[PDB]
Image (tube, coloured by chain):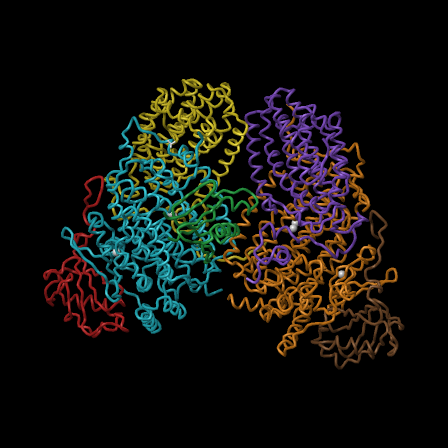
Chain colours: A orange, B cyan, C green, D purple, E yellow, F red, G brown
Amino acid sequence: KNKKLNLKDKYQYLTRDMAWEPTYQDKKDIFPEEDFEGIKITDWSQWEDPFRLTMDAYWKYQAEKEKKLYAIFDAFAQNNGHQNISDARYVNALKLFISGISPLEHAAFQGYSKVGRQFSGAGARVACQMQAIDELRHSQTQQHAMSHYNKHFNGLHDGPHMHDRVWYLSVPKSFFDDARSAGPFEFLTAISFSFEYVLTNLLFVPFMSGAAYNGDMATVTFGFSAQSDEARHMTLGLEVIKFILEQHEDNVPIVQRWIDKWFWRGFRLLSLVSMMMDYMLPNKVMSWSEAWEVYYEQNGGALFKDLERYGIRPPKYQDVANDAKHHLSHQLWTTFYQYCQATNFHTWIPEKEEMDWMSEKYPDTFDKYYRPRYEYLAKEAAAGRRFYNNTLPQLCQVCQIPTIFTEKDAPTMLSHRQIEHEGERYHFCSDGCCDIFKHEPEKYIQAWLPVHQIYQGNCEGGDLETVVQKYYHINIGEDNFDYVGSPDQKHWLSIK
Amino acid sequence: KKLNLKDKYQYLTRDMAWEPTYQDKKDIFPEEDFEGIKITDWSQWEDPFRLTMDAYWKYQAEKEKKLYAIFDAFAQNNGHQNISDARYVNALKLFISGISPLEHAAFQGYSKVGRQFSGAGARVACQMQAIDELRHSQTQQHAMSHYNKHFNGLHDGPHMHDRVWYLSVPKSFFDDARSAGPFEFLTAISFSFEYVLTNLLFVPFMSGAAYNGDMATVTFGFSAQSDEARHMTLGLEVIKFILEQHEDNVPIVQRWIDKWFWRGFRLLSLVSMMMDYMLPNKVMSWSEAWEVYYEQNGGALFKDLERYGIRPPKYQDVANDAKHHLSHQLWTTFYQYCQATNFHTWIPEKEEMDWMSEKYPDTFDKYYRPRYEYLAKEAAAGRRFYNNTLPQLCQVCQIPTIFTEKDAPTMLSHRQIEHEGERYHFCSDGCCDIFKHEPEKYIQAWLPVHQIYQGNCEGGDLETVVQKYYHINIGEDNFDYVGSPDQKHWLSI
Amino acid sequence: QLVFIVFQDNDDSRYLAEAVMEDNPDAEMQHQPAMIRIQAEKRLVINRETMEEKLGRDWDVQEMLINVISIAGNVDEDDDHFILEWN
Amino acid sequence: PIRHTYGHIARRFGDKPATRYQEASYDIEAKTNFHYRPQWDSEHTLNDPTRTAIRMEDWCAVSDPRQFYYGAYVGNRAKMQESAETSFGFCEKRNLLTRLSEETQKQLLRLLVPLRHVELGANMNNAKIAGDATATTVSQMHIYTGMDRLGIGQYLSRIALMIDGSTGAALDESKAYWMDDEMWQPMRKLVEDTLVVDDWFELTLVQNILIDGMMYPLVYDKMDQWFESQGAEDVSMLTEFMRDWYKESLRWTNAMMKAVAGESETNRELLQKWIDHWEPQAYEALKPLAEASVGIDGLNEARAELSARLKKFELQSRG
Amino acid sequence: IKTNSVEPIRHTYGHIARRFGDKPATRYQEASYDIEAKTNFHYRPQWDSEHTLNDPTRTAIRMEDWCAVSDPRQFYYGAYVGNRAKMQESAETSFGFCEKRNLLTRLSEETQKQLLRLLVPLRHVELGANMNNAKIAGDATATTVSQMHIYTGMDRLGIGQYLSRIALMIDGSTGAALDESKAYWMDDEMWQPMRKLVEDTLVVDDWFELTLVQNILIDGMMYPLVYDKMDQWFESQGAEDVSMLTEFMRDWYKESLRWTNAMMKAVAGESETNRELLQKWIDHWEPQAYEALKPLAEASVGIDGLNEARAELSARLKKFELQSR
Amino acid sequence: SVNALYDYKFEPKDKVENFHGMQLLYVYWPDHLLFCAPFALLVQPGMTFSALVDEILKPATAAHPDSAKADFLNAEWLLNDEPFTPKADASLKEQGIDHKSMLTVTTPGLKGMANAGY
Amino acid sequence: SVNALYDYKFEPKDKVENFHGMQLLYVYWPDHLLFCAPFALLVQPGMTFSALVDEILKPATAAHPDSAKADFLNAEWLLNDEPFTPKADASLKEQGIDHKSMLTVTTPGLKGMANAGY
Ligand code: MOO
Ligand SMILES: [Fe+3]
Ligand SMILES: [Fe+3]
Ligand SMILES: [Fe+3]
Ligand SMILES: [Fe+3]
Ligand SMILES: [Zn+2]
Ligand SMILES: [Zn+2]
């Protein structure tokens, strides 16, 4: 007889072969999106599937996974597992999470659903839609995971609301709107490749393993059950830039470009995580510095070592970002410290054996630059003079983070940058943020800067506090302010 | 015409049996006549639950997936560090050596009777009950399995059940039931134990483990009793069936009801201690727990039973008064003997005693607080007290003879008789009456204390028996909670 | 006198509690460990018809069986109900 | 406990414990303050409720009777796929399809397997919908149905593979009918056109209501009773999944027509406008297949039901 | 994902550690070994003068370690009910489908007869098998062995429910087919040698002589005859359609081989003494099995059917070093 | 009467013959529940009553603070709930203290601690 | 430069028009990282420099030890990086201090705490 099909071939007939050359409509009207970014795709049928689960397999695996995770959520809730966390300070990491990271889950569901329509290759479509509904799973799942903590702690009760509005959440809100507004080659590149491949561990492990080291059972279960999901997301990511670089030499400079952009946008987003893991986990996992060093400097080093063969090189300014692993987390925490009158999580001075640790993970920078800060701040708090800065900060036109970052090799100088464009001035956290601006200035001048919008009166209130309570929904006295004094702390001292 | 649920289950069940033409009915079922019970008509029998294998496998499996996800997560996550206090694990040490083996003896018991009854209905019910018990037995081996890895005294459960003194309390209980014929077995376990005192045993532990951060026990304890719901409505439905099957069965049923309630009750005493003492966070005075769970919920159902000509159990007044005393007596008993136990004991904390003075307003400060005061001075003086001389055991319940006369808390309710030239001793009249009905049975008991002295537990010391025979590690599983390797470990977190 | 039924203090059991509260004008609830106890006078009940209009799909008794720790009473089992009681 | 649920829920259903479906489905989406405008679309914004001319006070008036959040979707599908997996194991192993005559196999490869193509269509449509519609309760139901269609393609495709011993040749064959066969051209042009609708609610209507309200009953019911007489009763077992899938799809699609059409009579007449325009094209695409099969008083019997159940939203069609 | 760990005091329990070493052990291991009470019983059985509670000597077979018998399938309770839940679902699929599509009620009166007299009646055998396995589960000491008998006895109940259900589908839930069929079992001369054997097994003391007869000898030939041979033949008789209602049985049978052969092997390979016992019983018992099936082959697929299942089971005994055919 | 299915008859596991020429004695000291239950002592049938007192009971009751000033030899005794008068020099066995008898020994004026018989 | 399916032009969201008659100003004070980032000030184009320095900038800097002994105004300034020297009673507008400019005021001799620019 004729040849039985092999694995690859069988999967293609169960996906790609369903598609077909259109006859009654033009192809480009059906797929109108694949040209304006300037990416040329020579041959679609040379596409390699990143994974090969048919529907009945996906459904079967994912059902069995889900069943195990809701049993554990159910149990966790019925025994009040929240009481076993290491200490209520840890919950601020979940507040930052469900307001900050979790709505990104949903913007991905949204984004990949789209791109999973607009790609002409039927297989690029299934990988994406598959990713799409995974991200929807991630989003719903976190909502349940978090449900019980929401019932016992402050800060978590209006995630979606605050994501669209609260200043600091505009850092991740804007990241994603950047990508979803781009075209679909760049979306794949920013998210699958840049976020889901190069940076994914740098965001995932610190929360996931933070919860493990801190007695948070429901969140770590969500993590474990997400691994097999991420396995597929990462392969999609790395296949797909290999594919784009391969399908034409002119694709190359355009992709390089996207790499430098989204590495830098992602590095910047991540800085919230840096802080989270160094300052917010009562029990430490690893420093931000060792987390950068291992998952970016080494893993990413190797990743790029392999893409050299496509004429790709490692992202602009990575040396800035490496030099910053010794600072990032301390710089972020003082910022949030001094503005947490406006955040939906608490901050605090860390414990002395926390500082000792920091001294030990940052032997070149903690004691020189950062420990003095807490010594001062602690004096001041003892005197009933706990620092709050009442004057809003300058924001970066691209990353939207306050301009707290410093010159490489000069940790004492703010690395500010300023340009004119169309007789309008704009301001930047860094060379990186600046380079992204100059490359697409017509995009970024549209940014809804939270600080700026507050002064425009666009945030229902004429005093920061009025904004915070009415617009932000952040309950003054409850969601707000130092950990010390907080309703969460008292409620924790009852419990224990 | 078209069957109702009641008849369609029968066709799926009773109609597969048939009237034997080639062997005699009575050779095929030879255990149903000796006990004195008489069955006119096995078709009266009314299947309380209506499950088919497909339905049985489907629902149980759905329980198991869920149950093992949790066990796995608990382990993965070192959920043993979340227990209120390392004192608590001692309840679990008593659990796996004392109670889990009963789940197994049930599995054996019910498998057997699941063959012996000549009514096809009753067999399937027994058969499933039998398979549930095995599920209890394995799931616990599985639950306790993390606790065994981090704490002492759970590493030889079964081996200990067969040799350790105090464990012949539960071992002889089931040995009694399984050596008995099938209705007594069914009246003792399904009815007496499984229905009436089931609660009085599951709920104490289960809600306990609730309060003390122990997700794995509660998880099982609980999910592992949607079963006991079925296991109960067989208890109930089978005495109703037995009684109304022949006028004659009534007084035999009654005798049984008497015997098993008292056996039942004495084995329950162990729980009493544990619930008032090994729960660092308290849940409910053994006393409360009895009043609700027995006196009321119970005394209730012996109501729905006078209709069949049955009185409440004999000596039930004794066991109602006893509730003010049990836990204090049993616990001070184990306190002074825990050099020969796989588990630790201690003096309660000030706040535990206060709860105790409160829950036991008439008994505690009078009789038992001054015990702990005195024991505390001795301990601080460097004389923690251990009684170096074994106790008299009750020939029937096998418990040491520590109980007191009704309303005379300072006198032991000792009893003795002579039978064919031989002396025997008892904890109570309850225990004594049961002896007198069946002496040729109980004169067989392997009373641990005796056997240590017939020199049959492999040492001339108690210390050597404990080590080489019981497998108890002296210095580890043994002795006061204070100074124990459990203490040292817990405290370092 | 008072029949009863404990459930897992569960997500699903909220709904199972619910339905039993709402077609037993008298039953009285009470919480504890990680569990719901529910007793009442001589009798309780569990209609499939309740439950269905509160979960948006058909369901049978036997699902309920999953989440019950302990019962209390004589059994009246159906496709339509779960009556638990004394004569 | 400080509170029972999250604010956006408390705000919608009161301060008390909310259902799993509720905490997963309402008010999780980004809604306002978008940072830049789509480079791929001049008319609308990120997450924009006007990518349909339809107008709703609160899209959340469209919610799902089956109560699918992700977990309940997959756990349901898991159960269904298991069951079909049984079916296919049994057919395969008792050689139920391979044993049939080559004219009958051809019949399946011609009137049946080519639908994988319509299914592929539906799967693309739904992706556009799920990424277009703003309200999570809407968009989710679309990604679900999307993936169901692919999986349904997948089954039809598995029919082919059983027949050709997993070589492909029956796919090749069937796809050839799809492309070069007269009877499929209306159908195939109908599909290619839905691939170009912009209004996402026009698209749900055409695809999830009109086309499906007719082809489903035609194919997986009527054509089916008719296969018996053609010597193909044994395939019915590998199309149970499509029968239960449809019975279920009705629950949600009916509820979103009741809600979209009960809303504002100016909506009822945007829809009407569109039913007039497409139902026709759907009916036309279906006709050939009708006459190459159980014959037109299927199609009709089916248009019948469709216009029927349409009427329940006070829309209509004709006949 | 980095986790935090803990140094454990030990890895398993002492009985498992003694038996398999001080390393972590598997679920099956902790659920299955050294679990039951073994010695020091308090009172002798009132219902047996010959034996204590939990007595290896309820069978003439001896072994140093009954644990030497193990489930190749590794079933503790969960794994068991898990596997079966998956199976009973496939069956449910097939039964829904035979019904909605009327595939048994459409057959000719004469054909449905065949099912009523040739198949359904085995439920009486399955009922026998159930009681026999309950009896074993109750007498055999090692959990590894006893557990296996309870699972299978339960499965016996299940399979006879399925058989029972082919009839309800035929009579449409009246239960008259159940009745017609139960008369063939009691009354037709074709079923008496079978009925006789089944009742004779309900009166056998030795639990191993019992497992041998029932789970190796009777099943060893019945399932090949019935669920393979007479199954293909059915197609020739216009009743192909049933076959989807007997799939559970084929799957169940393929899996039974695995545990039964394991056990047969261990027990037979244990000693020349055990071998003489099996053989003595095989000689007494298998001709009886062949006899009990023989009328069912005559009325059916014919005697070759029987002879080949007879072969089939003869090749099995050879692997253990025993003979029949 | 046990019901059994054969003639149910068994030797007692606790026959003195099983004790390597020793016997069980029990002693209850009322009002001293410091000791939760009467002792089970393993004694020589040929030892003197005096020796019992000195060599076994003083030691077994030592831990109680009445033990030292108790005068066991001279206190109120029962042998199996019947009043009994010890002869200091008779062998236990020779004065009717046989296997598994219980002595009760009431001390006049020592009633243990608190007012709790402890 | 941006790539899109249409002419991709938009009005900036931060046009001075949007601030209701006011302007935005940035002020950065080196060596005083206690304030993590330069201030963002909603200011009057009109007011004077001295005014700005006392009504606004000084209060904003209060919390810092040096605020007091700094003489902002007589420190070195920068406007938008370019060296700069301010007219005390001049408006902001008129000396070229427009919407979104940034003053750097460096204050030599006051260089923050602990030799860490804090
Ligand atoms: O159908 Mo019956 O009730 O078992 O004879
Ligand atoms: Fe994700
Ligand atoms: Fe992902
Ligand atoms: Fe049990
Ligand atoms: Fe039970
Ligand atoms: Zn920036
Ligand atoms: Zn007793």
Task: Give how far across and how far down residue B183 sits, in percent.
Answer: 29, 43
Left or right of residue D127, residue B82 in this image: left
Residue A365 in view in this figure: no
Q: Is residue B398 above or below residue E184?
A: below
Q: Is B40 situated left or right of D122 in this image?
A: left
User: On the image, which quarter does residue A52 sit in?
Assistant: top right
Residue depicted at 36% across the width and 30% down the height: E214
Instruction: Evaluate whether residue F117 shows in this view.
Output: yes
Height in image: E108 above or below E317?
Answer: above
Task: Please name the residue shown 21% across and 64% down the image.
Answer: F28
A50 or A402: nearer the eye? A402
Closer to us: A473 or G85: A473
Above or below, F35 relative to D123: below
Q: Quadrant of ligand 1?
A: top left
Locate residue B409: give its quadrant: bottom left
Question: How many marks do you count on the picture?
Answer: 0
For the N terminus of chain B, the image quarter is top left
Q: Position of residue D13 (x, y in %)?
A: 61, 55
- Asked if residue G75 lies left or right of residue E128, the reply is right
Q: x%, y% of residue D76?
A: 57, 41
